[PDB]
Image (cartoon, rainbow, N blue to C red; front, side, top):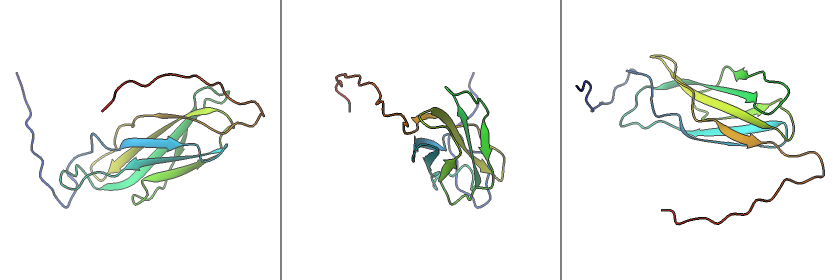
Length: 134
């Protein structure tokens, strides 16, 4: 059996929630206690829904505090956010999604980022050869 075909036209008023987007979510540690996450905007040709607002969240994966925070009140014109109030030299899982007038969306691919280090001790150096890609 097989139910469901392809072919979605464009419309002014959002139709359904996005599936792929947000995508290409690239997060980077702005400093030591601040993080910056940016994502790619949805296409127009097949715009599942007009992003009305963006939601971001972060939680220490390898930290004492396992409290996941959530940012509210983010402009839809901002495909990026600057998190402030985290630990230094610690990894954090940032989850950014896109909400539409039709409904909320599922979390996106989490990016592990390690904030700058405080101690004068530098991280390890693991060498490795890269195969043929592309």
